[PDB]
Structure formats: C-alpha cells, structure tokens
Amino acid sequence: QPFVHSPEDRYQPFALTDVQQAYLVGRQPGFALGGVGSHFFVEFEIADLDLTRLETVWNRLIARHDMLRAIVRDGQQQVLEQTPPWVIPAHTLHTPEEALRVREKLAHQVLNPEVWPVFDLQVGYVDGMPARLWLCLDNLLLDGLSMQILLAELEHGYRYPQQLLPPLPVTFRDYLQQPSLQSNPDSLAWWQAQLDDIPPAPALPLRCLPQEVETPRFARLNGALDSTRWHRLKKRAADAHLTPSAVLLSVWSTVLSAWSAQPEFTLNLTLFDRRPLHPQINQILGDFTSLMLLSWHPGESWLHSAQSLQQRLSQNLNHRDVSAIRVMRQLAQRQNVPAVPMPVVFTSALGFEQDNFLARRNLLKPVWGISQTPQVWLDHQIYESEGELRFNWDFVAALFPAGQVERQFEQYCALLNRMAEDESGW
Ligand code: NA
C-alpha cells in the first residue's frame, strides 16, 4: 500500500479523531468528572539561558511541525500556513517564591483550541538562580509520543543550534486520510462477544462525588526504578512469560485491588504506536492515541493473575481498531445505564526508541510537571530513559481521601522494588 500525499489540501480542514472529540467534550461537565482541559505542562531549569537561541529553536520547530500550527475550528482541525513568530514572554523574578506563583498560574491556564496558538511557552529569570522555562502543550493536538519527540528536538536544537533538519516528508493530516484508517471487521463482534466479562473501573474510596468537582486540578507523584532493578525486573518478566508492561500493570493492579471495593476491575490502556504507512511516520507530531480496555481478575497467586492478564492483553491488542470509547458505549447499552466510565488509566511510552528522553545531563532540566485528562481520576504514566524506568501518577487530588493516593504510591513503589530484587512473589 503506497502512501497518498495531498499537499494541495495541507491547510484544509480535516476530521478530529475519536480521542480528540472526547477531549473537546471533556471541557464540559461529564458523567465522571467536571470539565477540564487536556494539556501537558513542564517546568525546565536552564543555566545561562540564551533567550535568542531558545527563540530560534522554538520557531524552527513551529515551522517544521504542522500540528504546532493547528487549531480546532468549526468542529474540525486545521493547520494554519502562516503564524506570527512566537516572541517568548520573559518574566523578571527576584525570589523562587515569585517564580512559584508564576508557575502555578501557567500550569493551570486554559488553552483555547480555537485561537492559535494552542500552546504556551514563557521564561522566568530568577536572580542568582537558573532561569525557568514554562512549556504548555495540548494532548488534544500532540499525543504523548509526539511530545517526547518535540521535547527531544527542543533539547537537541538548543544544544546544537547550528544543525538544520530537512523538512518532514509526511503529515499527520494525510495519515488520517489514508484508507487503512477507514476500513471494523470481526473486531466489533469480538468485543461485543464479551461485554458481560468486563468489570467496572476500580471502586476506589472517594472523599466526594466526582461530578461535584467543578474545577478539577491535577497533581503529580513521580518515581523511578533504577536501571539495575529495571533490567532485572524485565528479565524476571521474560522468565515468567510476561511482557514488562504486563508486570507493571499487574503490580499496579495488586495495589489497586487492596483499596477497591471489588477486587476485579477494568483499566483503560493508552497506547501510542502508529500504523507503519510511511517510513518516517514515527517522526511527526499528532494524535495517534489508541484506547483499549484491560481487565484485572485476581487469582490464587500474583503470577497466575499476571499471566492471565498478559493473555488477555495479547488478545485485546489484536482488536484495537475498535477503541475503548466504543466498547464503553457498548457496555452502557448492555447494562442500560447512561454511561460506563473508565477513569483509571495506564499510559505506556515504552518501546518507542526515545532512549535518553529527559536525560540527566540535559540543558533543559525538567524539575516539575503536571498533565490533565478529562474524565480521568488517576493516570499512571510510564516511560524508559537512560536504562531507568520512570513513572508518575497524575490524579485529581480533591477526589481522594487525604493521604490515600500518596499511600498507594508508596506501596506500589515498595512492591515494584522488592519484586525486582526478591524472587519470592514469582
Ligand atoms: Na493531558
């Protein structure tokens, strides 16, 4: 199948993906949460910031990546051909407390997707301290993998500002227009065949009704598993006939089981892999997200339920052309309820060749970040960098009893490290 380019329609409107549609309606009150945006915010520290150089690098990226010039207009998405160069706002701050107040303001801003730009990038100079770079990107337009690609290019361009990259020979707009993305065969039937075996989302203790949260604010807990333990864990996984993702999903689900009203539950898995329709498809920015339900059914031993989860994961992956968005509608109809939410999410950026993403010695040193997703209470995100497994839980703090998420994270980290070191649980 040869890829079909349409350069004459590069700036014409094109349809939103299912995920993008869900994000847009997620700005309003929903069945599982109040309205909230969908952006991704990171604060960097830069010693000896050269603003002119950073501005050059960032504007080159805007010109290079069509979806940085994209907007949502009249219920569709559209790439703007020419946008005014981004002149980086710079704040002059005297104390880190002043910088914190700016961080808090920018980290919870509302990106209006109808007016370019659907991003924000500002800098803050702190007297006698490294300068701050506050970057806000929207998952409505750039998925998790895309933001790793963009952040690595930003870091690379700032370190080596003399290098010029050749233009990209393929666009996200054309990718969505390809025939493969318009072909559901037995996948819809296969999912419908097991609606009666998909339990609800984790029944975690709440401190209030999630709909009674008018302005959801996300918080982050982050951790890492050292490279020696991550290597050993992946080896134990292989010996146990499990993928690394299945092990992490199984360790996480064990903690979630201990807290939930029912031990069995269903998670929503966020994946980023792309159909290989063009040899450079993995270099571009866009929304390639696929959503897939995965159910945890505990057994006698952790290993049994992990192996059972792996098998289910392998089968489910063979039917991702039917997204979890549709399966949740099918579940709601079979159960005669208005909606079946899945607000507990696992997001994996493993296996995408982004080695040394946010590497230790980066000039743009990440120090603080947060991400928001509508209709999601708890989002466990993972990626690998420098041989190390890095993870973070993004969650609506106000939803849960004080100390609860912090305690689950503590238990999860402890269980993760012990199973990497101790052969007992296997
Ligand atoms: Na987000």
Image (cartoon, rainbow, N blue to C red):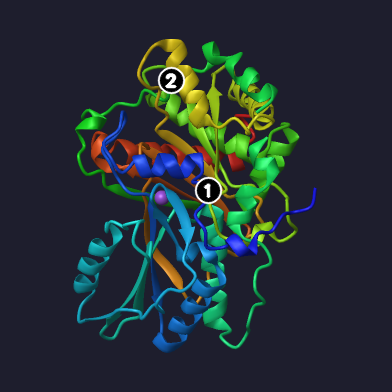
Q: Position of residue 290 (x, y in %)?
A: 56, 40
Judge whether residue 413 can be spotted in this image. Answer: no
In the visual, does 288 lie left or right of 282? left
Residue at x-position 53% and y-position 23%: 296
Which circle, 2 or 1, is nearer the viewer?
A: 2
* Residue farthest toward the front in the current orientation of the protein: 8
Q: Amino acid at mark 1?
A: Ile
Residue at x-position 49% and y-position 34%: 252
Q: Is 367 or 159 nearer to us in this picture?
A: 159
Q: Amino acid at mark 2?
A: Pro
Residue at x-position 66% and y-position 58%: 282
Q: Position of residue 200 (x, y in %)?
A: 43, 20
Q: Is mark 1 within 8 Å of ligand 1?
A: no
Cα gap from disc 2 to disc 1, whole angstroms: 23 Å
Identify whether 85 is placed above or below 200.
Answer: below
Element carrying mark 2? loop
| Residue at numbered disc 2 | 200
